Each structure stands twice: as structure tokens, then as C-alpha cells.
Amino acid sequence: EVNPPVP
Image 1 (cartoon, rainbow, N blue to C red):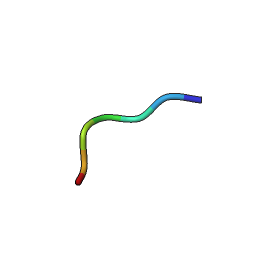
Image 2: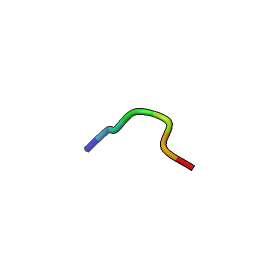
Image 3: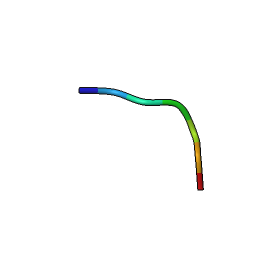
């Protein structure tokens, strides 16, 4: 899967 930048 792939997700947005959420550090």
C-alpha cells in the first residue's frame, strides 16, 4: 500500500 507523509 501507499500513504501520504505523516511523521
